[PDB]
Each structure stands twice: as C-alpha cells, then as structure tokens.
Amino acid sequence: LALHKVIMVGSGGVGKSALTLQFMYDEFVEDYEPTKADSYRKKVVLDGEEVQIDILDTAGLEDYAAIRDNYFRSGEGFLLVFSITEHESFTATAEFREQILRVKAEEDKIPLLVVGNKSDLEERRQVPVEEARSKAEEWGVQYVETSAKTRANVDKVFFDLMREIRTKKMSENK
Ligand SMILES: Nc1nc2c(ncn2[C@@H]2O[C@H](COP(=O)(O)OP(=O)(O)NP(=O)(O)O)[C@@H](O)[C@H]2O)c(=O)[nH]1
Ligand SMILES: [Mg+2]
Image (cartoon, rainbow, N blue to C red; front, top):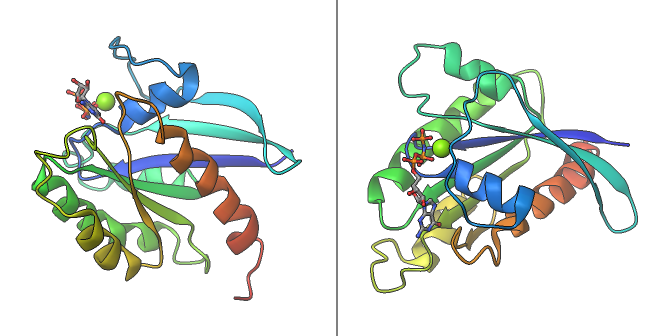
C-alpha cells in the first residue's frame, strides 16, 4: 500500500476544497469543513494496484509568513489548482510554483499537476486553455480544464497525480 499525500496548492482563494469534496462524495454541496491537521484517507485502485491517498486542503496561505510552507513540506505531491474566471489565480499560483521546490530542496523529482476549475463557464473564460497549457508546460506538467459543478474531470487530477508520482518519483532517473 502506497500512502501518497496530495496538497491542494494554489493562488490562495480559488476553490481547491471544491475538487476535494467532489473526489470524496462525488457530489457538489457546500458545508465548509474546518482544517488544521485533520486529513482525509481512503483506498483506491490504480491500474491494478491499491494505494492510499491522503488529501489535505489548504486555505488562504497568503497570510502566514512561513507557516504555509509546512503544508507543502507535509506532502509528497502537489496540485496547483486555479480558476479561469479569476486571472489573479493563475498568476499567484505561479508564485507558489517556485515555493514548492523550496520545501523539497533535498528531493529531485517533484510531482506536480495544474488544473483550472470554473470550466463550466466557457463564455466567462479569460484565460485560454491553450495559453494555460503552454505556460504551465514550462514547469513540466500538463494543464487540464475541470468543473467542480459537473464533477466530470475533477477526479482526473487526483488519479493522474498519483500515477505521476509512482512513475516519476520512483524513477529517480529520467
Ligand atoms: N461554478 C463553480 N463554482 C466553483 C467551482 N469551484 C469552486 N466554486 C465555488 O467557489 C466557492 C469556493 O470559495 P470559498 O469556499 O469562499 O473559498 P475557497 O475558494 O474554497 N478557498 P478558501 O477556503 O481559502 O476561502 C464556492 O461558492 C464554490 O461553489 C467550480 O469549479 N465551479
Ligand atoms: Mg475552501
């Protein structure tokens, strides 16, 4: 059993928790769960391999001075999630990107995945999907569109992330 910890990193006020709920109950509902140290654990099969997945949502980390870094150093994988309706998200999210390597200066292969919610609004999309893939590709990841309201491809970023870890992280070569 491979216990992989995913950190919902982002700008600071997008909606990472949203994708967090959809992956847990596959249902769009507002309840707001207080976070401080409590994480979510469950078992899911991966191409014929049952591994553990620990999710830990992170609120506005743009408040703490360095306490925020802890949330990133407490996890192996990272998920940079932002919103298309908020051009401020994609920008701030870019800043955190560099912060990820800081907490993992000892590590080499750093698993990451970028995604943009609010995709349910193709008419209110300010950031072109193609433009988001190119910029994000620089970091070494693939960007995808998702809708926390349709819960269609929300789980895609969760499963794909883990797969990237078992392959890239365990590689330590390529
Ligand atoms: N239509 C739509 N609404 C979304 C999506 N993701 C999040 N939302 C909405 O955005 C809001 C979430 O923001 P909020 O809970 O205030 O804060 P947050 O963005 O979770 N981060 P924080 O917990 O730090 O405040 C909710 O109203 C939720 O329904 C999405 O993909 N589509
Ligand atoms: Mg939240």
